[PDB]
Amino acid sequence: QTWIWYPGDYEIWLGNQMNNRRTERGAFFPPFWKTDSHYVVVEFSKVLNLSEPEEVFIAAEGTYNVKLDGKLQFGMPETLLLPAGKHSLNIKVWNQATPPTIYVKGKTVNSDSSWRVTYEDKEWIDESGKASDTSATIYMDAGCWNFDGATQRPSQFSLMREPQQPVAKTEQPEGGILYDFGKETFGFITLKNLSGKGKIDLYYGESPEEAKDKAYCETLDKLLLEPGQITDLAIRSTSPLHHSDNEYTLENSKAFRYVYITHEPEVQIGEVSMQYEYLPEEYRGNFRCNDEELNCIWEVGAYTMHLTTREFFIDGIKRDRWVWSGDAIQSYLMNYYLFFDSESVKRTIWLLRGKDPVTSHSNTIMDYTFYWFLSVYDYYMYSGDRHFVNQLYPRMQTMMDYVLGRTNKNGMVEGMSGDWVFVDWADGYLDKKGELSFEQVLFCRSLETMALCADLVGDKDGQQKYEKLASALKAKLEPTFWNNQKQAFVHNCVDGRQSDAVTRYANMFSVFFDYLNADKQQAIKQSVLLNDEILKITTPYMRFYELEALCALGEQETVMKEMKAYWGGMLKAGATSFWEKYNPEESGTQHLAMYGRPYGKSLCHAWGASPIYLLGKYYLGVKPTKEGYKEFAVSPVLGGLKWMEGTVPTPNGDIHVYMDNKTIKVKATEGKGYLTIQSRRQPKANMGTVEKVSEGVWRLWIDSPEERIVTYRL
Amino acid sequence: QTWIWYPGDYEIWLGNQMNNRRTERGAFFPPFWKTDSHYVVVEFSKVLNLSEPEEVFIAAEGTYNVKLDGKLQFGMPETLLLPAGKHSLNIKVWNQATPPTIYVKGKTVNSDSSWRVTYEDKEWIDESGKASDTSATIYMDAGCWNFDGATQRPSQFSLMREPQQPVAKTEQPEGGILYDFGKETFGFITLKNLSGKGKIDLYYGESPEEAKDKAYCETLDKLLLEPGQITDLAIRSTSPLHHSDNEYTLENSKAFRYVYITHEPEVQIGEVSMQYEYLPEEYRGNFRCNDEELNCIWEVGAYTMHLTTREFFIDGIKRDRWVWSGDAIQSYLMNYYLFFDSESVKRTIWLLRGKDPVTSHSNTIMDYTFYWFLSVYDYYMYSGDRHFVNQLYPRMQTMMDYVLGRTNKNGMVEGMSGDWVFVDWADGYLDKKGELSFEQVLFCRSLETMALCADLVGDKDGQQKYEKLASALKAKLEPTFWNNQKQAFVHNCVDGRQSDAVTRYANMFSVFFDYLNADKQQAIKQSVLLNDEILKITTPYMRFYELEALCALGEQETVMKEMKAYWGGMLKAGATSFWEKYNPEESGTQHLAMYGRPYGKSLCHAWGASPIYLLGKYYLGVKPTKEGYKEFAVSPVLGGLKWMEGTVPTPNGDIHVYMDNKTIKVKATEGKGYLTIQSRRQPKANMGTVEKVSEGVWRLWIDSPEERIVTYRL
């Protein structure tokens, strides 16, 4: 048994709670897009056929009633005896404050996802006493997480805490002490042994410059110490203090490496430490090679991912600390090569979608609506979780309804009033008007995704509709955006006119989406991907995809050179977590500014950890080829490295890969698949038969957890 | 200044709270239709142009921030200094538990309906620091009621209480005491001077039979008295008790006339009384004639209306005690001739509509969706409140979208899966399949209403659409449902085939909707309205409309005979409030049963007070002819009475009417209009000119508050 609720409703409520924890210099800062709510009245039900009478314990968050075979029980019973035979247990709950949720426990009757929920049962009695026909009522399978204890109330969920001490403190000339915690971290400040009275001010920073800048630092706190109590002035919450040995831990979490603290004359602070907050995670994925710089890049990437893997996958810990679609899709991917936390992926997907009616694109960003669609099928391929797709499908349909009612005469998408056509942070060089080739590519992929999901859930009318729309748009891509002279997809079209500008976005995506044939993909490699004439990318975010394209075209060596220079560049700049944006042309404090503010840039953004994904999927070369890794593919490439080794998690297994200049070892504890080897002459295998795919390329079919060892020579 | 919120959101939240107070034998009983929620994050804003600096006080229910000219203030300030000049004050609030709401007060800056609210501002900052263009953002005028005090938190609203003592108590043979409160009433039971320990059981009833029937009474309570405290077992809420002189008032309200109380041996109850709960109301309407029976009918009707006029207009106080569309539209009408509480009308209209997306008809009842539409224009005609229509319009459009996507090949409405085609409680004699003439008549009226509202708000595209649809459906009414042989509209059509059955519903409505010409209206009078061959009506609900039709055809004398017999019949049966249903053929305890339960019938249903409306509009003969009574019409008819006199409220005035067999007096303190007199020869007026309309009919134009006196002789 476990606590259950209407699917997606707990996630939405919990997401609102977390997102609304963002602050800017002491002020509450909710998202600018619409905030949705859970359904305040829901009915939980379960049809029972018991061979023997059993008693169930009932717990719930909210006001509720209990109906057994149509008969309303008195009040709110905590236990109910269930007779033998066929019965129908119905529990309707009302909860405006937190999501309606129940906990039922018995010998055989237990609350779980096999229970059905609805927010509109429509059962009424006519004047004779006959109940209405509710066979038309729509039900959903109940949602749940891991709250298996009767006392583990879903609404009280909070992340784990762990004590930490700073590694340095320095008194400042203008007063106060500047604490260095060693590296980017996240948590609650603890002040031990407070005495006296007066104000106490906290100033946080991811850099010493931000922490010391009391007037422009992004986040801070202001407290008032009084005899026997202290008060958080920002939220006006007074907590009690013991006169003897006291301790006060701030109520709200903050991201930071440095914390500058000051206080009035009559205040005395014994000790300053913190409570590191985190979501328990198992580092199931792993990677390391001879290049120690890359090793550090991977480690820093993993740490960045963990800090940004909280109640949901977020953009950054300092600023925004909200769930964004563009960032999230990459988090899911990096997650598949690190934690493989499928539960977090689903919670984030539920949250980003929100509820109906649809009033705008995801986060109001057009391209973000498409990432959301793509992320669902990506999750299915890696987890094999068909049930999730079935539960989300209705909401996927209505989101696509919104998009499809906004296409133009060519069936393409153009930014409309209220839309944000983002693409990337390219310093303002990108034209957002007309039909961007990049957006149609994403849109086309979204239609293909919807077609594949419609097929998975069995909606054939929908499937046909999406396939027809996807096929028509796809056939228009080259006739519309391809340019023979530039040998690439132009940036955009306005009134049917191609722009002189060619950006790398539509081109790089067309490579791993496979929208271009072999010949044009190679053309793009030279005319776009390796052409420094084409506008460069300055965010780890799009380098994720730029480099992925290159890896798809087998340019792992050039990519290695780029990853080392780009990410290693942030390290050499003092990074202990990867940033939101990085231009190696800038220097010093310039790296800290963004959004027109001196310390506006987040120095810990989920999308800065790109390497986690690139190395796992293109160097260790692992990826599922059938949902949930029912079937996989391992195509390792060293790309300059002498030796590398790693692990890639799967639903119920792992794929270990080792490789040096003459040997490859693979141990797949789940599924079957092909190990592809690039060699001059035929490789030798300790198992199975090595088959020649083509010139210089070989394959080996692995069909068991027994480690395979092959020797080759490129 | 006053507390403000997103329009409709407070009403919805407050409505959920009230509706969910219904109980059945101790069990919480929420509605079977979907329960909507308020938006949990809303932004309040006001553009200011101050000639001098002023400080405002700020209060709010929920977490909030304050932004002045784009600058986020620290924490949650309770006061803010506003500089002279142009500024923009923005307050974003988050409240999941109760509706986000704020209170601002200054010399000139005050929270009120002139403030704008949105649940999606969409303001974002690009990487340079430039704010997005939010000129496309949709805003609404803030909603409000009468919470003008800084401490009058909207979420704490509750109705007035007034002490009351029972008028009789009788010990019962099977134990306990049966208390008679004299008449149907509503409130909380108070138990003074409790001592001892043990259970205490309450059993409520609108009849002594129900109260004494511990096993089948609709409502009850169970308490546990303990030393120093007592506990409500149904809701598990323990309250403290003083050892000396204590007093405990039950936490939940109940409808009842009789209360049967028992308790264990060791319990001792000093005194039993109650707290009558009610919404403060001014009896602005009034009526009385020579017939003292009708006078009592009007009084009982008024009392029934008041008991059912709580936080919203409800169906009945004992059972359901929910807001239903069919009942509500009649409540609004009876209200215009009694309290003229426009605020209650708007709150109920907001509540019944709920939020988007639309998942079913109002209360899931097809005909109830149409009443909702009609009630909006009815409210406009009587109150002149155009602003309300403008605010509700978007929701009206989406409700009509739902209906229009459910029409058949003839553009008519047929009950679909999940729909409840109600019409009336006619004991199961009404066929609900096919195209009911009654539903198309209501539907057609709904389209005409939407056209008139579209016109009022300025939506011309919509107006044209609705007019076209209304005109096409209207022209199909007679060709489809009229039968020459039966001289009436048949009950329904199935596969284009008329039913042999003719019910009075479509016919009576076509009379006051004016869908039939003079000749057919008279045909209906004889072949339907006065033909006892046609199925009779047994609910006060439809007699409201049946009798109204007859009054429209000037049969006030037959109606008088019906009202006296029908309503006077319930009085002679012991009613102190009018019922949900009444069949004068039944007798004794049969009058108490419904829904297959012995005491299932509500003996206090809003729709049982029909006379309030009939007498005010058709005997005193008053009605507005231009919104808000800008222009009125007074056409008094005695219908058997010797003398009658009354008052009809208007937004800012009243219309007093007096009439006997030779004199008519009218004093209209608002608007202008015609007084129509039925006389053999020309009447004489103390003012203005008496003009002859037609044979035996005269008119007089009243254009001032000066009382007019005319003498006539029928």
Image (spheres, coloured by chain):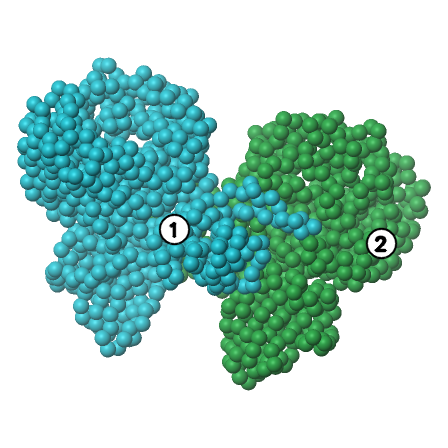
Chain colours: A green, B cyan
The answer to whether residue B125 is seen in the rendering is yes
Amino acid carrying mark 1 in the image = Cys
Chain letter behind tag 1? B
**Within 10 angstroms of label 1, few (less than 14), some, or many (20 or more) residues?**
many
Q: Nearer the viewer, residue A190 or B384?
A: B384
Does residue A76 appear in this view? no
Residue located 84% across and 59% down the image: A293
Q: Answer with left or right where residue B357 lies relative to residue B190.
A: right
**Disc 1, SS:** strand
Residue under the point 55% across and 66% down: A234
* Mark seen at residue A565: 2
The answer to whether tags 1 and 2 share a subunit is no
Q: Is residue A542 left or right of residue A708?
A: left
Q: Which residue is drawn at the image coordinates 53% and 50% (left, top)?
A: A35
Kind of element beneath mark 2: helix
Q: Is residue A108 above or below residue A499?
A: below
Residue A29 point in image, percent of width and height: 57, 57
User: What chain does badge 2 belong to?
Assistant: A
Left or right of A110? Residue B303 is left
Which residue is situated farthest in the bottom direction here? A244
* Residue pointed to by mark 1: B144
Q: Label 2 neighbourhood size at 10 Å, few (<14), some (14-19), many (20+)?
A: some
